Amino acid sequence: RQLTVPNIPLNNLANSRVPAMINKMTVSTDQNQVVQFQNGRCTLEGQLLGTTPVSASQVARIRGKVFSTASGKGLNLTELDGTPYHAFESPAPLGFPDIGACDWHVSTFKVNLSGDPMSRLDVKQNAPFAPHLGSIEFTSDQDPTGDQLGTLAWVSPSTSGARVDPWKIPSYGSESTHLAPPIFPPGFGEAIVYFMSDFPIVSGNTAQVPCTLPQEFVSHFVEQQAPVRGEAALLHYVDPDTHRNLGEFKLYPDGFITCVPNTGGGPQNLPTNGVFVFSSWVSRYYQLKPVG
Amino acid sequence: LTVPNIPLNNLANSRVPAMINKMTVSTDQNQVVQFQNGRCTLEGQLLGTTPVSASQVARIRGKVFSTASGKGLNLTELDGTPYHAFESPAPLGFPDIGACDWHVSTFKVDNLSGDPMSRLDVKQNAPFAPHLGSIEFTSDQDPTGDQLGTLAWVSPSTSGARVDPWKIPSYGSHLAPPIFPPGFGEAIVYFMSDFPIVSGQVPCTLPQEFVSHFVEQQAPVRGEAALLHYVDPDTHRNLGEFKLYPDGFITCVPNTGGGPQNLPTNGVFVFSSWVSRYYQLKPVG
Ligand SMILES: CC(=O)N[C@@H]1[C@@H](O)[C@H](O[C@@H]2O[C@H](CO)[C@H](O)[C@H](O[C@H]3O[C@H](CO)[C@H](O)[C@H](O)[C@H]3NC(C)=O)[C@H]2O[C@@H]2O[C@@H](C)[C@@H](O)[C@@H](O)[C@@H]2O)[C@@H](CO)O[C@H]1O
Ligand SMILES: CC(=O)N[C@@H]1[C@@H](O)[C@H](O[C@@H]2O[C@H](CO)[C@H](O)[C@H](O[C@H]3O[C@H](CO)[C@H](O)[C@H](O)[C@H]3NC(C)=O)[C@H]2O[C@@H]2O[C@@H](C)[C@@H](O)[C@@H](O)[C@@H]2O)[C@@H](CO)O[C@H]1O
C-alpha cells in the first residue's frame, strides 16, 4: 500500500484535541518547545497512540456512570460506547480530553427524557482526577444520574488568578499512565507545525487549541495501514485551483508534520485553503525550503 | 473504489454530533426520507447542506441582531465567511432535524470571561428562515456578536407533541432530493445514534466518514451499484451483503422480522465489486 494524505483542504479538517474545525497553521513562539499531546497521535503505519480515537466525533468526549460519596459525586468512566473501561495500556478511555492543568466543563445527557436533559459537569484536575484508574469527580448545578455521555464544552483556570495553557496535558494517574511519547522538533532548522482551532477558553492567552495532526489525517492513516518506506514523507501544500506548490513539509513516521519557517514568519502566513499532497519518501536529513 | 476501513461503531452520524450505535431499516420499508445532511454522491458531490467534516455537522454560526421580540442570528458559514442566500438550503452543516425546537450551545468567537456559553432556544415557526440567512431565538443568557455553536438537544414544538427526527425543516418561503427505496425487497439502511430528544435515536443515511471519503476520492462510478460486504474485523467473516448506490445511500434485503439491526455493530464495510441495478442481495438479519 502506498502512503497518501487526505485530499481535503486545511479549512475542511477537524482539530484532533477539541470538537472544532482547523482555521490555520502555526509554529510555536519557542521553536524548541516539546509537546506531549495524547490526542491526535498516530503513526504513519496507522497505529493509534495515547487516548487518540478514530472519529472527529469521539474527540474530547466523556462517558461514565454517576456515583455518590460522602463528599460528593463522580463518574466511573466507560468507553464512549458504554463498554467497560479497563486500565491497561492507555492513559484514559479513548477520546478522553487532554487539555491539561485547568477546570473542564463537560455537557452531558443521560443515555424517556423530560424537561432539561443536559447537565454541565464541572471537573477539577486535582487529587480525585484519576482517569487512568477509571474515575473522576465533578460538581454540577444540575442533578445528573446514571449513564452520562458528553462533550467538553469549555475550559477555565484551575484557580482564580491563573490561566489556561492548552499546550499542556493532564496528569492521568493518582503510577505509569502509558502516555504517547513527547514530540521534539527534529532538527535541520525544522519547526513542528501546529493546527489551530477557535475554542472557548476562559482566561487563555488566546481562545485557540493546537493539535499536531488533523483528525482526518489520523483516520486516514488508520484506514490505510500503509508501510513506511523512508525516514520521512515529503509533502507539498498545494493551491487546489492553480495546482501550485505553496511550500515543502515533512511528515515523520511517528506522526507529526514540520516545516522550516522563514524568520519572523512561518506557515501562519500561508493561505488556509490549500491541500497537502504526498510527494516522495526522503532521508531524515532532507533540507526543506523555508516557508512564510 | 473504496469505502472507509473503519468499524461501524467508530463512524460518526452525519445529522447529529454523535457516534453510530447501530443500523436498522424503517418499520414501514416504503418510507421516503429527504435528509439534507449526510448527502453525497458516490463520485464525491456534496448535496443539500452536507459538510465534509464530522465537526461541521449540525452547527450554527451567526451575528446577533435585534428583532421585534428579542434577538436573532444573521447566519454566516461556520468558518465565519459570509453566507450567500443562493443554491444551498442553508449554511453548510446547518442542522436538518425538522419540526421541533432546537437548543443550540454557542460561544462568542473572540478574550473570554465568566461563563462563555449561551443556549439559544430556537423554534421552527414563522421567523425561522435559514435559506434567507436568519433565525430567531430566546435565551436565558445574553449572547452578543459572532456566536458559533452546536445543536445540543431537541424538544417538541408545542406541549403534548412528539419529536420525529425523521423529518427535515422548512428552510423558508438545491435541496437534496428524496431517497426512494428502490424495490425488490430492498430497504434503505439507516444509521442510528443516541441523542438527547425530549418526548421522542436520530437516523442518517451515510456515516459522515463515508461522505468525506467520497469527496476525498473523487472516484469514477463504474457500475450501477457498489456491492459491499459487512465484515467481522476479528474473525474476518462476511456478515452480510449491502448495495451502495451512486446517488449516495445504502440498502440491504432484511430478513422478515429482522434486518441489519440484528448484526453486530463493530463490523467493517468493504467494497467487493460493481454490480447491476437489479443484483439480488442475500438477505441479512
Ligand atoms: C466555596 C468558596 O469559598 N467560594 C465559592 C465560590 O468560589 C463559587 O463561585 C465562584 O465564582 C468565581 C468567580 O466569581 C469563579 O467562577 C469560581 O469558579 C470559576 O472560576 C474558577 C477559577 O477562579 C474556575 O475557572 C471554575 O471553573 C469557574 N467556574 C465556573 C465559571 O462556573 C466559582 O466557584 C467555582 O465553583 C465552586 C463550586 C468551586 O469549585 C470553586 O473552587 C470554583 O472556583 C461559589 C461556589 O459554588 O460560591 C462559593 O461557594
Ligand atoms: C410564566 C412566565 O413568567 N413566563 C412564561 C414562560 O416561562 C413560558 O416559557 C415556557 O416555559 C416552559 C417551562 O415551564 C417550557 O420551558 C416552555 O418550552 C419548553 O416546552 C416546549 C413545549 O411546550 C418546548 O419543548 C421547549 O423546547 C421547552 N423549553 C425548554 C425545555 O427549555 C417555555 O416556552 C418556550 O419559551 C417561551 C419563552 C416561548 O418562546 C415559547 O414559545 C417556547 O415554547 C411561556 C411559554 O409560552 O409562557 C410564559 O408566560
Image (cartoon, coloured by chain):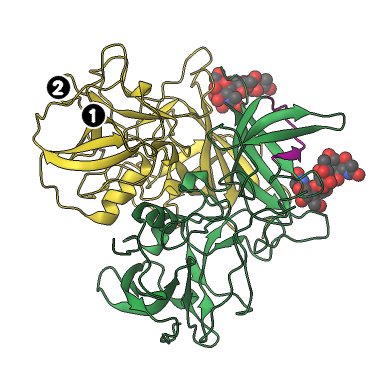
Chain colours: A green, B yellow
Residue B230 visible, this angle = yes
Q: Is residue A177 above or below residue A232?
A: above
Name which residue lies at 10% across and 42% down.
Answer: B223
Give the residues in magenta. A134-145
Q: Label 2 neighbourhood size at 10 Å, few (<14), some (14-19), many (20+)? A: few
Q: Main secondary structure of the magenta part?
A: loop
Query: Can marks 2 and 1 be said to lie on one chain?
Result: yes
Residue closest to the eye, A128 or A200: A128
Q: Which residue is mark 1?
A: B251
Q: Is residue A69 above or below residue A262?
A: above
Q: Quadrant of residue A286?
A: bottom left
Q: Is residue B162 above or below residue A203?
A: above
Q: Label 1 neighbourhood size at 10 Å, few (<14), some (14-19), many (20+)? A: many
Name which residue lies at 49% across and 74% down.
Answer: A268
Chain label for disc 2 = B
Residue closest to the eye, B242 or A139: B242
Image quadrant containing the C terminus of chain B: top left
**Residue B183 got which mark?**
2
Q: Amino acid at mark 2?
A: Gly
Chain label for disc 1 = B
Q: Is residue B220 left or right of residue B57?
A: left
The quadrant where ligand 2 appears is: top right
Q: Is residue A143 magenta?
A: yes
Residue A196: percent from the left, percent from the top? 53, 63
Q: Quadrant of residue B203?
A: top left
Name which residue lies at 35% across and 41% down.
Answer: B131
Secondary structure state at the residue bearing disc 1? strand
**Residue B9 got which mark?**
none
Q: Quadrant of residue B271?
A: top left
